[PDB]
Amino acid sequence: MMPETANIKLGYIPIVEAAPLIIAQEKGFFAKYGMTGVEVSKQANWASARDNVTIGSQGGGIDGGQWQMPMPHLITEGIITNGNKVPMYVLAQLITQGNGIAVAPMHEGKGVNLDITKAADYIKGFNKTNGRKFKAAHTFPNVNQDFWIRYWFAAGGVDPDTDIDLLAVPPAETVQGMRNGTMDAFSTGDPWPYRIVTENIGYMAGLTAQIWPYHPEEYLAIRADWVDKNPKATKALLKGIMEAQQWIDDPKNRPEVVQIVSGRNYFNVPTTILESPFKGQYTMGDGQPAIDDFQKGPLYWKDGIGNVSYPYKSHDLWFLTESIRWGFHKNAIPDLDTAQKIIDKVNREDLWREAATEAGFTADIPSSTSRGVETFFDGITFDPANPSAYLQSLAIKKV
Image (tube, rainbow, N blue to C red; front, top):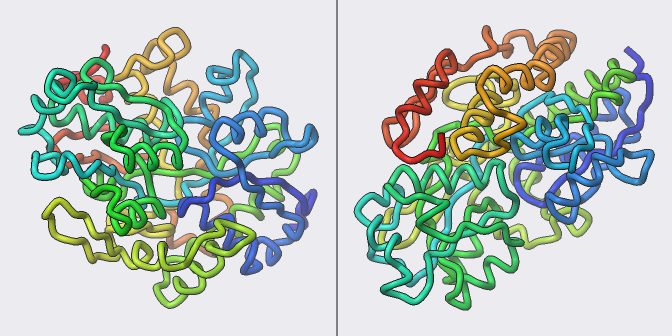
């Protein structure tokens, strides 16, 4: 099925979530299906990734790439691009887990761990007791990592909007702040946790693998105009990604995966900082036991619930439901019906199914577009069939 074109520019951020794109390219999986002209382009930050996909490859940007959710949806509706609507299609989930919340040393022994309920008053009154409002950061508002730390805070009784200072700050600057004693928490992901702990910059309150096991995370999304014009090439790219994900999850191949992504032309970091996490090994600190479980590390093809790669529409729904929870994009996404309408235009799980079928991976295709009821660490459940009930079960929200 000769692709219409063998070329495409896909952006990535130098974190473990990018692995499938890098491996599909470097191990020849894209080439196997005819996509011999794939350029895996490093993005400076999420803002730059957003801008680059808006201009497209022809304008000097990118045709698609790696994204935190629901960026593809927000770009499609021009919500985060000042009204410039650039339709995109979510084609596959790249990975699950590999994210976590780091906390500064000064908060050790205060109960600021996975469940911060007992430390809620300590956090809320930090200005009076310590001279500043508890300060936390993520690197881009209204997406994955902002959601993770907001859920963690709110589950313990801390309002992330009113009780603390939750800011969007570059990763290096944030870590520097933690070292300087001016930043209290950081919603981040591999390879950051290893460095933060080993360099005694802070400890890990919890992994997203603990907050929501096998949670939806990073996704591959490409501009709709590119996909509509190159349907065969799109499926070829999906097959390459699928094989790369399958390859990455075999423990035998992980040393090579680590070696490749850590290389100078990609992440450009010492392999040592990624070796442990790729084995599901994390030193958590604050007197808590270390984690040594492959199932708690990043997973790219299959997880404990189902297939990782398949993009369940129920997950798109959770991201937009949580957006509504925090009052994000009030005018653009005023209700759950509007959210579903956006999801039906953006999520292209049908192409994932088609590509998987053509490639001979029919045994791995999920039977539904929903992964069913989702369960969080605090007992809250999200039933895709009734997002209203989920929202109403939450203690802290803006709706």
